Image (cartoon, rainbow over all chains, first blue to last red; front, side, top):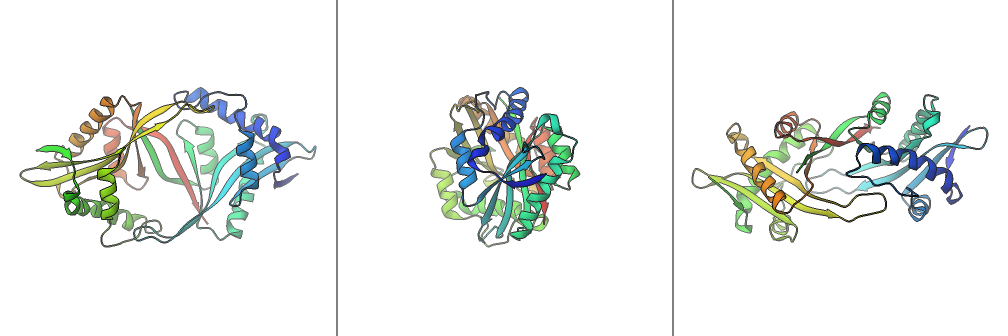
Length: 156
Length: 156
């Protein structure tokens, strides 16, 4: 129905969506991620909502239920001797309810992030995604995103 | 041929190697990287050499030139509600002289990094590499490294 900015009163619905994605990461990379109740710290959520450079978006359906959310950050680095000045929207979180994928919700949310980025005349949108996460990768790829760089690892 | 810790007196030889890698990145991703003379800040080099958690290694051979260097960091994150405790060696820089490729130098340097990681009983060695850099990616893969996660981008 609509995409709006979240408020602090959206914590419980957002936190539930956060747990779906977090537990999937715990399952695949338990060497890095740990289970907890809650998985979303409400103080961290409050800071994201009220932060100067961060924005929390939610997709709300016709029944006033939150179906997806995203957290984004306006990032600016100045001109340096060896690095260009750069302005980006960084997506730290984007979760679509597990039972509501394939309904176009994720694309709608991403289009809102694009609109925001253009309004702020940013150079690019960026995010980070784990290699095991084929669902996320195919999603971002289908929307035109491409790999900039990667973290490589060798367990000892 | 030896691998030893660098000192501040190794600045110029190391800076030259840093420049080779940096200008390759300027050429391929000039949207992010910028040319400068020098590309390696000597105050930053000194801090890396003398840093509590950083180590700079150099490969010296043939009498008596530096053919490669690397900068590594001991990284420790504590147990958190949603993240496991983790200890790693992060490689922030690794440059083998362009003119000295195909001589087993990169592997020798990496083996010394592995030894360090083992002495410090770390969980993994990690690094970041740009997607355009097929040579570095293939080389790191040939050492057994694998993609953990990636940064994706969409220019606007």
